[PDB]
Length: 62
Length: 63
Ligand SMILES: *[C@H](CCCCCCCCCCCCCC)C(=O)NCCNC(=O)CCNC(=O)[C@H](O)C(C)(C)COP(*)(=O)O
Image (cartoon, rainbow over all chains, first blue to last red; front, side, top):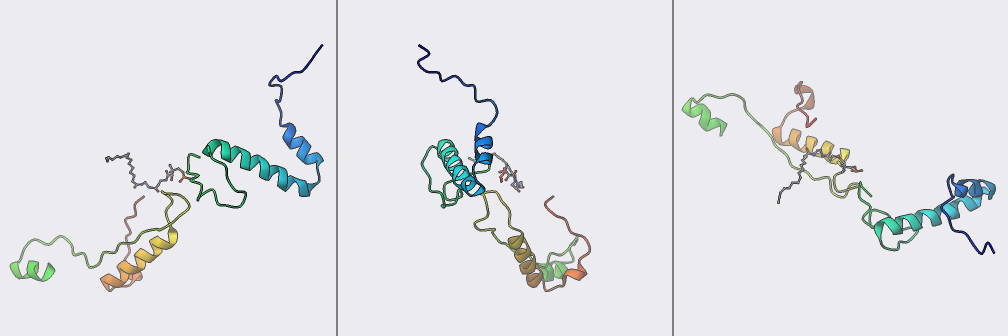
């Protein structure tokens, strides 16, 4: 009967704890994916993981 | 022109002997300054004025 839940109960960064649990090599990939996602969100366009943010227009405010 | 000013005996406050212009190029951002470009324009001004940096004792920076 509970079906599902989606409430904003994230609070503390479970991302940080899950990365800490994961081996340090994995930390690079997870951080890479998080940064790519957030930068694509803020710059409104998808990005490459190696192209400079400068060539993506990341200004001072960005 | 300083020779003409001396020739006509006009009031002279000070003489400028060299001016230089330089651009930072592609810095980190659109407003980021370049230390290397500033040093380059300083060298260009010194060369154009025909004078040594040790001679100058007062510097009026952008600040
Ligand atoms: C000159 C400052 C003059 C600014 C005047 C703003 C006028 C508004 C628009 C005029 C419209 C004209 C009408 C035409 C139709 C100056 O001496 N610059 C100050 C020194 N310049 C710099 O060093 C840049 C200053 N640095 C910053 O504050 C940062 O770069 C910023 C704010 C961009 C943020 O960080 P980001 O660089 O990481």
